[PDB]
Length: 290
Ligand SMILES: CS(=O)(=O)Cc1cccc(Nc2nccc(Oc3ccc(NC(=O)C4(C(=O)Nc5ccc(F)cc5)CC4)cc3F)n2)c1
Figure 1 (tube, rainbow, N blue to C red):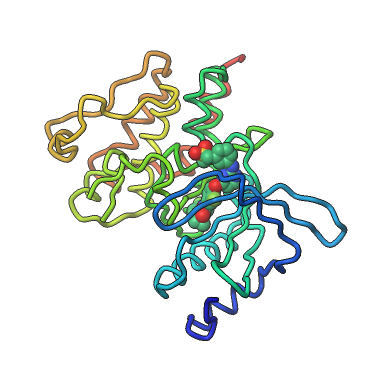
Figure 2 (spheres, rainbow, N blue to C red):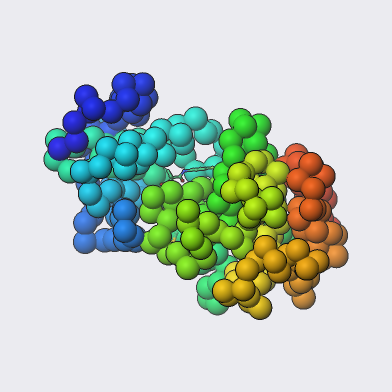
């Protein structure tokens, strides 16, 4: 029971271009992927016009009483419609119902988020595999940067992994508190992934995404260790300003660590572009047999 008339008409227009009729979507309410303060995600089945069943994730708000929340929720989904790249999560559509929250419907990602995948001891990715995941993230980010899209929360916890081990850059947005909320510090900011200038100004750019990408590479090379295990409540800005960076992981190749240090250049202007990152990491990846 949202009132579409109260929303920005341009937003409603965009939503209608990706509408899923409620009868085409079955939400498995008993099968919850996650729950947070603002939202929740369920398994779902989407029927296409030919009757083919598609396994999907279905994201919902917990409340629909605040127009800002409803508008932001729909806007987050609509933003994704503008993305078409193998390493960027795509939108299946948005289901508007006569009762309750609109539903944002995403393709199902078998292996969940990249951080949970690499931390899972039942999986055994090689150093080459892990570098490959990093390369895929860089390609997704190269695409997004070309669209002048600034991510603001790039981290392994926000990237998804499908059944073919394709990494999809994503962002849980309003449902980000479902998992790993403790990495957010009071604005809720992912301080251990943020560039020095962003810690100081709370402004983000593609060059600050590059810093976060460096941290993501470190996550990959440590199979999902928390960054800066030396610091919990100690101010990360002060820590960095003492002249410190994350240490080189034991199995991180020297040139990949050099890439990380470049991503953390004190001058944003001097950090490599995602184009440069894709080129450099492709070369490093290519040196591994397995
Ligand atoms: C992640 S986990 O390991 O902790 C839990 C788990 C375990 C096993 C399987 C899964 N499968 C799964 N498949 C598809 C989606 C999904 O959850 C979502 C993953 C991402 C989102 N994304 C979004 O809501 C948005 C988004 O991703 N935007 C966005 C922003 C920038 C981009 F570059 C791309 C997309 C619109 C805000 C929404 C979701 F419901 N979850 C999930």
